[PDB]
Image: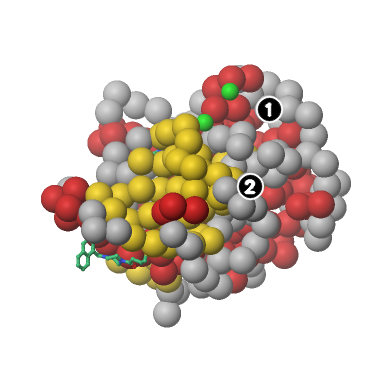
Amino acid sequence: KRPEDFKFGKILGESFSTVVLARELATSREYAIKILEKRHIIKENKVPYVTRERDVMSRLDHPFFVKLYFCFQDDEKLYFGLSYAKNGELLKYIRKIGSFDETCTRFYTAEIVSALEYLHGKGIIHRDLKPENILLNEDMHIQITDFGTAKVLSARANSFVGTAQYVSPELLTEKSACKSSDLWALGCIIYQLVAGLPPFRAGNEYLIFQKIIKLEYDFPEKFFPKARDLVEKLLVLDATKRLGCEEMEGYGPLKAHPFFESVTWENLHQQTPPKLT
Ligand SMILES: CN1CCC[C@H]1CCn1cc(C2=C(c3c[nH]c4ccccc34)C(=O)NC2=O)c2ccccc21
Ligand SMILES: *SCCCC(=O)N1CCN(Cc2cccc3ccccc23)CC1
Ligand SMILES: [Cl-]
Ligand SMILES: [Cl-]
């Protein structure tokens, strides 16, 4: 595919990339085109993010994931053609409506779990999962994105990445990520859906790091009991003891948690999501 094939429309967002809403003229398909300046990627020292983003997304084929449909270049630019998620970031919705009812919390948590199971199945660790990175398409189904910081396992691995609010303990104290590290993030995300704020809150990132390793957070009073129960089984310092990790026997037990007991798992992507709170 060539640049000339697209209208480059509204700039959807702008650090070392600009994401534009593009329309392929002949098919009228919309894509989110990520535009990168080769030279600026070099000077900011972000080539690893780009190559890694490409490698990982090229392995993904699942409804709950943004897909990499095409890549092209010209003399000064790199163009990534991605799935366009028209409804933007999960984060926007939590800020907008405050916190989700249990029906919505349950459904979206289910889709994220379903997504993680697939990702981890292919031996990939996201490492930076968060509401900003969980997008909603036109059908209001999730589409995860931002794989630049991901890791392909050969287990565990070594790297220095994350977002303070969702970073797992093991990343901070062993400088190593595993699949269970994503389950920690999931725990933080469920909490935030229900409470309307992330669980670990402090004066700065280092202080946030301290909360995390201290397991220092609180459930407000209105927290759905079964969700509280699930969150406690995910926010566990010992990475080998989180619900859904390999030592805990995997996703079977995670999906069997009472919080999910009503969920119809196999065709989540084909169900009309619940009206958002
Ligand atoms: C740079 N950003 C703006 C705010 C947060 C961050 C966006 C997170 N994000 C959103 C992405 C995507 C999309 C976006 C939809 N609305 C946006 C607004 C700003 C930036 C991106 C998007 C999308 O349609 N498909 C996507 O894959 C995306 C694709 C690759 C890496 C990170 C991404
Ligand atoms: S769109 C087709 C795929 C492009 C692609 O995979 N890559 C790999 C990452 N680089 C690194 C890079 C970036 C900027 C300038 C470069 C000059 C020479 C060699 C690599 C460069 C290229 C695009
Ligand atoms: Cl948005
Ligand atoms: Cl909006």
| Corner quadrant of residue 225 | top right
Please, is residue 163 above or below residue 207 in the view?
below
| Residue 70 appears left or right of 268 | left
Q: Nearer the viewer, residue 127 or 180?
A: 127
Q: Residue at x 76, y 52 (%)?
A: 269
Element at badge 1? loop
Q: Nearer the viewer, residue 250 or 141?
A: 141
For disc 2, the marked residue is 28
For disc 1, the marked residue is 100
Please, is residue 232 above or below residue 219 in the view?
below
**Badge 1 local density, few (<14 within 10 Å), some, or many (20+)?**
many
Identify which amino acid the numbered label 1 is placed on. Phe
From where the camera sits, is residue 196 visible?
no
Give me the C-alpha separation between circle 2 and circle 1: 34 Å
From where the camera sits, is residue 257 visible?
yes
Q: Position of residue 199 (x, y in %)?
A: 49, 32
Q: Position of residue 71 (x, y in %)?
A: 43, 62
Q: Residue at x 45, y 66 (%)?
A: 56
